[PDB]
Structures are given as C-alpha cells and as structure tokens.
Length: 149
Length: 148
Length: 149
Ligand SMILES: CCCCCCCCCCCCO[C@@H]1O[C@H](CO)[C@@H](O[C@H]2O[C@H](CO)[C@@H](O)[C@H](O)[C@H]2O)[C@H](O)[C@H]1O
Ligand SMILES: COc1nc(C(=O)[C@H]2C[C@@H]2C(=O)O)ncc1N(CC1CC1)c1cccc2ccccc12
Ligand SMILES: COc1nc(C(=O)[C@H]2C[C@@H]2C(=O)O)ncc1N(CC1CC1)c1cccc2ccccc12
Ligand SMILES: COc1nc(C(=O)[C@H]2C[C@@H]2C(=O)O)ncc1N(CC1CC1)c1cccc2ccccc12
Ligand SMILES: CCCCCCCCCCCCCCCC(=O)O
Ligand SMILES: CCCCCCCCCCCCCCCC(=O)O
Ligand SMILES: CCCCCCCCCCCCCCCC(=O)O
Ligand SMILES: CCCCCCCCCCCCCCCC(=O)O
Ligand code: NI
Ligand code: NI
Ligand code: NI
Image 1 (cartoon, rainbow over the protein chains, first blue to last red):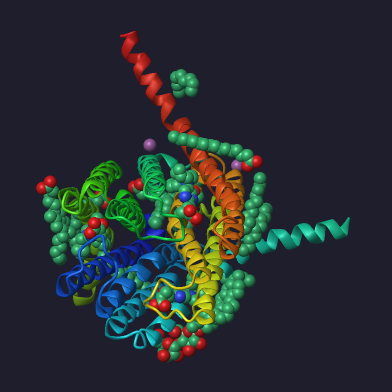
Image 2: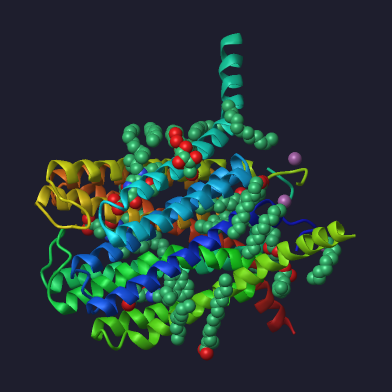
C-alpha cells in the first residue's frame, strides 16, 4: 500500500491492450476453424492456400502484437494517453480488416496492411516525440552550459 | 528519484513474468536438443514428426507469451496482484505440461492446452472486471447527472 | 492527474524499448526487400536459402523481442535502470550483428547469436537479483521471527 495509485493514468492503454488480446483470440478461433474446414492437423502449418493465408494473417498479427504494445505504452505515457489509445484502436481495427482481407486473398490484405503500418508508425512517432520532450531539454542545457564555460 | 516506489505493488507480477522467461529458456533448450538429436540445421523448421511437435510447442508458447504478459499485468494492477499472479502460475505450469504432452504426441497436448486456455481466460476476465470497476462508476455517475 | 510522475525512472527503459521496435522495423524492411529480390510472395515462407536465412533471422528476433522486453523492464525497475538499459543496448546491437551475420550465412550468425544470449542472460540475472533483494529480507526475517518464538 501507498496512498495514491497511477492506474488512472493508464486505464485507456490497459483497455486497448485488452482489446488487442481479445482480437488475437478471435484470430486464433478463425485459425482453428480453418484447420477443421481444410483438415490441417497440428503440427502442420502448410496446406491449401485458403488455410495458409488465414494462418499467416494470425501469425503476422501475433508477431506485431508486442510491438504494438510496447509503442502504445511508451506513447501513452510520454506523449498523451488519449491520443495513444486512439492510434491503438485505429491499429487494431486495421488489423481486423487486414485479417479479413488476407483470408480472401493476398492482394486484398494490402490496403488494410498499409493502414496497419501507418497507425503503427504514428505510435512510433508519438513515442519518439515524447521521449525527445523528456530528454532534449536537459541535453541542450548541458551542451550550452559546456560552451558557456 | 522520488521518495516512494511502486515496486512493491508489482513484485509478484514481476516474479511470475521472469518465471515465464525462464520457462521459455527451458523450451528453447529442448528445441536445440531436438535439433541435434534429429539433425535439423537452421534455417530449416521441418523434419521428423518428433522434431516438429517440440518445435511447434515452443513456437506456440512464444507466441502466447506476450498475451499472457499483457493480461497478467492488467489483471494484476486493476483487479488484484495476488490473484493475477496465481492464475499466471497456473498458466505457466499448464504450458510446461502442454509442452511435454506435445513432445510425446499431438493428442497428449490437448488436456494441458485446454487448461492453459482456461487459465488465460481467467486472466482475461479479471482484467476485464478490474477495468469495469475502474470505468463504470464515473460513467454511471455522468449519465445520472445528465438525466437530472 | 497527480503532482508527481514516474516517467523519469523509466525513460531509459522506454528509449531502449523504442530502439528495439525500430530495429524490428529495419528487420522487416530487409525481409520485404528479400521477398522482392528472390520473388517469394506471401503467404510462402520457404524459398532460396538467402531468403530463408533473412526471414528466419527476423522471426527469431521477433520471438525473443517480448523476452527482451520483459526482462529489460524487470531488471530496470528492481535492479538499476541504467545498467538494465545498457545490457539492453548490448542485446540489440548483438541482434543487429546476428541478423547481418545470418543473412550472409548460417555459420556467421553464431558469434553474435552467442553474444545476444549472454546479454539476455545478464538481464535475466539482474532481474533475478533485484527480485531477490526485494523478497529475501522479509522472508528471512519471518523465518527468524518464527524460530525466535
Ligand atoms: C526515430 C523516430 C522515427 C519516427 C518515424 C515516424 C514516421 C511517421 C509516419 C506517420 C504516417 C502517417 O500518415 C498518414 O496516416 C493516416 C492514417 O492512416 C492517413 O489517413 C488515411 O486514413 C484515414 C482512416 O483511418 C482516412 O482519413 C483516409 O483514408 C486517409 O486520410 C494519411 O493519409 C497518412 O498520410
Ligand atoms: C492459451 O490460449 C490458447 N492457446 C492456444 C494454443 O496455444 C494453440 C495453438 C496451439 C496448439 O494447437 O497446440 N489456442 C487457443 C487459446 N485460447 C483459445 C481461444 C481462441 C479461442 C485463448 C484463451 C484465452 C485468451 C486467448 C487470447 C488469445 C488467443 C487465444 C486465447
Ligand atoms: C537470445 O537468447 C537466445 N536466442 C536464441 C536464438 O535466437 C536462436 C534461434 C536462433 C538461431 O538459432 O539463429 N536461442 C537461444 C537463446 N538463449 C539460450 C538458450 C539456452 C536457453 C537464451 C539466453 C538467455 C535467456 C533466454 C531466455 C529465453 C529463451 C532463451 C534464452
Ligand atoms: C504493422 O507494420 C507492419 N506490418 C507488416 C506486416 O504485418 C506484414 C507481414 C505482413 C504481411 O505482409 O501480410 N509489415 C511491415 C510493417 N511496417 C512496415 C515498415 C517496416 C517497413 C511497420 C510500421 C511501423 C513500425 C514497424 C515496426 C516494426 C516492423 C514494422 C513496422
Ligand atoms: C504490457 C502492460 C504493462 C503495464 C504496466 C503498468 C504499470 C503502471 C502502474 C504502476 C503500479 C502501481 C499502481 C497502483 C495500482 C495497484 O497496485 O493497486
Ligand atoms: C470480454 C471479456 C470477458 C471474457 C470472459 C472469459 C470467461 C472466463 C472463462 C473461465 C472458465 C474456466 C473454468 C474453471 C477452470 C476449472 O474448471 O478448473
Ligand atoms: C511488460 C513487462 C512489465 C512492464 C512493467 C512496468 C511496471 C512499472 C512500475 C512503476 C515504475 C516506477 C517505480 C520505479 C522504481 C525504481 O526505478 O527504483
Ligand atoms: C535463475 C537466474 C539465472 C541467472 C543465470 C545468469 C547467467 C549469466 C551469464 C553471463 C555470462 C557473461 C560472460 C560475458 C563475456 C563477454 O561478454 O565478454
Ligand atoms: Ni499507510
Ligand atoms: Ni529528494
Ligand atoms: Ni507514485
């Protein structure tokens, strides 16, 4: 126990984070359901194209999920909670469309893939700007103090 | 520096996290050892079924690891540290049995897989309840104030 | 809102985290570029060895990213911010060399792979020591108080 909590500075980030977990659960579910429909038994990860695209979509979302996370949280703490959470949401909605697109074809994944990438770059930029705002003043000051002597 | 630290509210979550890291290390070690026994040289990922099942078991535990993490932390902060840590432990022990099961066969993976899924779902539910507790009162209040 | 922030205790961790995200971006970019040069269209993940090595290097770095993250943060918070950040940087730089090595051959990946593993074990050790320093005193004290009664 302390007599204050910082929950209330990260609750939006936490909500978006959870939403991302749930979205991954939906993607796994679709993979399970593709495994049944095209009869691809674990441990195999190859099969008909229609299976491979679903499986790949899920794998690519899972692999980007930690990156999404890390940049969400850095942006949301160093830049602005609300703005990070919102880019997060745009990221997740884009990945849902990416997943749906890819299921249909390689080509129909592209537009939402690009939109996923833009939303993730926005998170990167907000995180970077936030970190710059945190470190740049002291560093400029130290450099000016050095030249002043 | 501040004159207080919040470490002590997250130390169980941190211990469980690290335990999870160590478990992944054990899984990688088994994969390395299966690569030697069945002579599957990187960058190959395919080979005899006994190699593929170990390899897949590891890749599936790696891929769910961040999900475990995220929910572990959200649940532990917004619901209850101890309860989240404990579900976490149950998740990790279930994955260790899943890994061992899968090595032996596709079929023996299933019971511990299901247990691992139940444990993760519990973490999800805790995280969701914790977030509901945080947001719901102010939202109901704002709505009541609007109607007044 | 609050009248203190803990940003300034984790800014180095956050910066190393973001550097890690950027490095994964660089790795993906090399994968895209290898897909074009060797004509391997998603959803395929197999192709000429030169493509497979790049692709594997990227996958292995993505899969260890969250482990790196988790241990970076636990070490940075329970042991020492600066020392964790520094081992983080050595981890990332080694993975860059691992990636470049692996692109050229299976064999050239090994030295920087071993350096990546050492740097991650150091983070694991710093995390474990920090957790020990947090829990061990109260536990020893409780055990002694029990025997004293
Ligand atoms: C070391 C630090 C490195 C930092 C690097 C940072 C790079 C930052 C790049 C940000 C790229 C943002 O680019 C911008 O993305 C948005 C969001 O999709 C696009 O917006 C687009 O999507 C939205 C839907 O969500 C619609 O309004 C419309 O379809 C379109 O305008 C812009 O058309 C594009 O120009
Ligand atoms: C541990 O959770 C899960 N693990 C696995 C495997 O590890 C499978 C691939 C390995 C194999 O076949 O051996 N699969 C499904 C799992 N579920 C089920 C959910 C999809 C309906 C899940 C339960 C709770 C939350 C979740 C969040 C995201 C994804 C899933 C969540
Ligand atoms: C960076 O650490 C490791 N990286 C890789 C690769 O990236 C391999 C797949 C790439 C290739 O072969 O090209 N493999 C094994 C690694 N080890 C050592 C292992 C004995 C447990 C590890 C060292 C330190 C901590 C760890 C934690 C979890 C898993 C592993 C940890
Ligand atoms: C979501 O961002 C990205 N996603 C994907 C896929 O999910 C691909 C594998 C799926 C497929 O082809 O179906 N690829 C590239 C992406 N970019 C592009 C950037 C690297 C040049 C990225 C944008 C912003 C930050 C980033 C950080 C790391 C990696 C990438 C970052
Ligand atoms: C991947 C998600 C990681 C989330 C990390 C969030 C940690 C910030 C909160 C500090 C912990 C203390 C806040 C008081 C809450 C409590 O313990 O009751
Ligand atoms: C939108 C978020 C809500 C998600 C709710 C997830 C449901 C929790 C399911 C838990 C079922 C586990 C059954 C108990 C385990 C056992 O019998 O040993
Ligand atoms: C994804 C792995 C977990 C991320 C963990 C973030 C937890 C942040 C806890 C609050 C940080 C402030 C306390 C700093 C203590 C110190 O530096 O001495
Ligand atoms: C339960 C916690 C286990 C901790 C295991 C830690 C293993 C640490 C090994 C570090 C080896 C460092 C040797 C480096 C030599 C060099 O880099 O030049
Ligand atoms: Ni008190
Ligand atoms: Ni002071
Ligand atoms: Ni505080």
